[PDB]
Amino acid sequence: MDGEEVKEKIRRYIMEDLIGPSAKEDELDDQTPLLEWGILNSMNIVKLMVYIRDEMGVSIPSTHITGKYFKDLNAISRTVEQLKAESALE
């Protein structure tokens, strides 16, 4: 329930673990097309799914995994806060 704290955590983990070479100081931006970079697919996306799960405390269901939310980092976080609300009542 912040947006920014969630985003900066995730985006930087994409730079640390996921990518490697194409992950300079400002390669991964706030609005970067993550799917057009093709960095997010079933192999990679699960390391994010567990990252948000532990760090943000948000259980992302497998049925939630669709392009619109994993499209850019704002779309990532906005839906994390929705799923955070779901997990808050659950």
Image: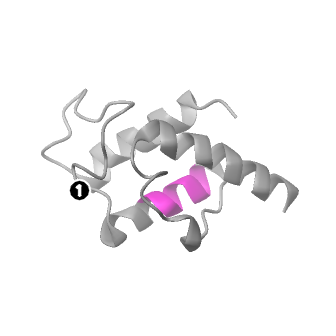
**Above or below: residue 46 compared with residue 78:** below
Quarter occupied by residue 30:
top left
- Residue 64 in the image: x percent, y percent? 57, 64
The scheme the figure's colours follow is one colour
Residue of label 1: 38
Residue shown at 15% from the left, 43% from the top: 22
- Residue 88 in the image: x percent, y percent? 82, 53
Where does the N terminus fall, quadrant-wise?
A: top right
Task: Identify the secondary structure beneath mark 1.
Answer: loop
Residue range in magenta is 48-55
Residue shown at 32% from the left, 66% from the top: 41
Residue shown at 65% from the left, 55% from the top: 58
Q: Tell me which amino acid carries mark 1.
A: Gly
**Above or below: residue 7 compared with residue 65:** above
Pick whichever, 28 or 64, lies toward us: 64
**Above or below: residue 10 compared with residue 50:** above
Q: In this view, does 35 lie to the left or right of 55?
A: left
Q: Is residue 69 left or right of residue 55?
A: left
